[PDB]
Length: 302
Ligand SMILES: [Cl-]
Image 1 (cartoon, helix red, strand yellow):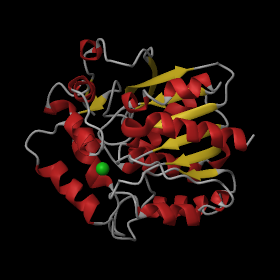
Image 2 (tube, helix red, strand yellow):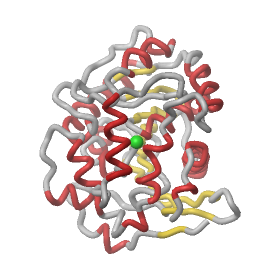
Image 3 (cartoon, helix red, strand yellow):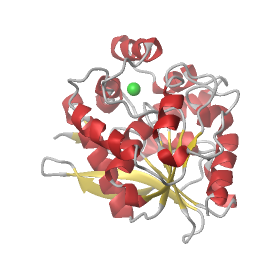
Image 4 (cartoon, helix red, strand yellow):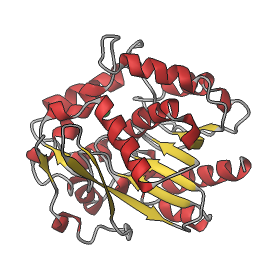
C-alpha cells in the first residue's frame, strides 16, 4: 500500500497540547510498516486510561481530559488511528476497513505494552475499542463508553447518522475542523479548527477520513457483520466495570445509549452519568467533566 506522512511543521505550536509525540510501528497488512502516533502522560506506574478518538478527529480531542487524569494519579495514553492525527496515512480508501483499524489499533496497544486498561472511547474510538474489548476482554479492567456504539449492521443507524454519512461523501472539500465544530455545542476557536485540519494539508491525506463513514455497518451484509456479532456477544458476557457517560445533545449516538447500557452485564450497579450541555464531540464541550466522571469511576472500582 502507498502511505503518506503529514509533515511535522503542521503540528507546530498547537494550543493547550504540550504533550510530546511518541510513536510505534505496526504491520501495514500487505508487507510494509506504518507509524502510529500516541501520547503517554502521567506516572509511569499509574493505572492506564486509554483514550480513543474517532472520525475525523485525533488525540488533540483529549487535550482537556489528559491533565485531569494525570493530576488524579492515572496514566493517560491516547493513540491516533491510522489515517488521522500524527499517524501515517494510507492513500487509498480501499486500504481502510473495520478489520484493518481493529488490527492496527490492537498492534499499537500491544507494542506500547499496555495492561489492565481503562478504555475511554467515543465515535469510531468505540466502534474499534468496544470490538477490542469483545475480542480481548482480559486486556481491559474497565470501560467508559461515551457517544459511541458497536453496530453489527442488524439495526437502522438512525437519520442523524445517515445525514452525516451523506455529507461526508458529498462535500467537495472535507473540513475536519469545521466537522468537529459542527458536532460541538461550543464555538471552537479558529486555532482549534486549525489543529483539526493540521493532519490534512490536502485531500490526498484524507482517504481514511472519507472512508470511515462508509465502514459503519448499517446492513447485515457488511464485511464487519460476522466479527461484530461475535464481539457483541462477548461484550454481553463482560462482567467487569462498564460506565455509560454519553452526553445529552448528540442525535447521532443518543439512541445507542440504553442498548449498550442494557447489554453489558458489568454496567449493572455502576453510576452512569449523562454529560450535560455537550454535543457529539463531548470532550470539546465538557472534557473536564467527562474526565472527572472517569476518575470517580476508576476510584469506585479499585
Ligand atoms: Cl463516521
